[PDB]
Image (cartoon, coloured by chain):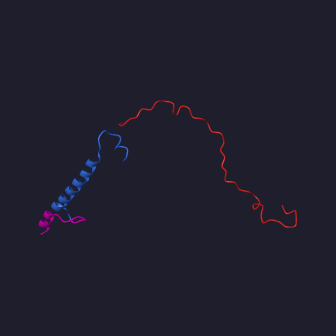
Amino acid sequence: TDETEEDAIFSLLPLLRKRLIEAHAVSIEEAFMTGDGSGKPKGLLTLASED
Amino acid sequence: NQSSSVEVSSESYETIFSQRIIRDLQKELVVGALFEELPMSSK
């Protein structure tokens, strides 16, 4: 919101953007590790188990 | 009207419509802007 930016001494935007990107990377790597098949890529461990 | 021989179409076709806009008296404001102002840059 455009009021918490003024309602503080230091900025809070770069933290927001960096959190967005790093959350995205964490989720993709976790899904590649052990994602199921329901709307998400089948994880390596799931492939190994089902083979 | 329709008193003479010739006439006009409707009673709204001899009226002058003015776009002048008038407003009544409004209360004055006193306390709103007589105190000194203190800028703030935080909560």
Q: Residue furthest bottom?
A: A51
Which tint is chain A?
blue
Is A48 contained in the magenta span? yes
User: Quick one: quadrant of the N terminus of chain B?
Assistant: bottom right
Q: Residue furthest top?
A: B35
B30 sits to left or right of A20: right
Which residue occupies 83% across, 66% down?
B7
Which residue occupies 60% across, 35% down?
B28
Give how far across and how far down residue B24 sits, in percent: 66, 42
Q: Residue furthest right?
A: B4
B16 w.r.t. B31: above or below:
below
Which tint is chain B?
red
User: Quick one: quadrant of the C terminus of chain B?
Assistant: top left
Is A11 contained in the magenta span? no
Give how far across and how far down residue B27 sits, in percent: 61, 36
Which residue occupies 67% across, 53% down?
B19
B21 sits to left or right of A13: right
Q: Quadrant of residue B2?
A: bottom right
Which residue occupies 56% across, 32% down?
B30
Give how far across and how far down residue B38 sits, in percent: 42, 32
Q: Quadrant of residue B18?
A: bottom right
Q: How many marks?
A: 0
A40 w.r.t. B32: above or below:
below
Give how far across and how far down residue A26 sits, in percent: 20, 55
B41 sits to left or right of A15: right
Image: magenta residue range = A37-51
Q: Nearer the viewer, residue A20 or B22?
A: B22
Q: Nearer the viewer, residue A26 or A43?
A: A26
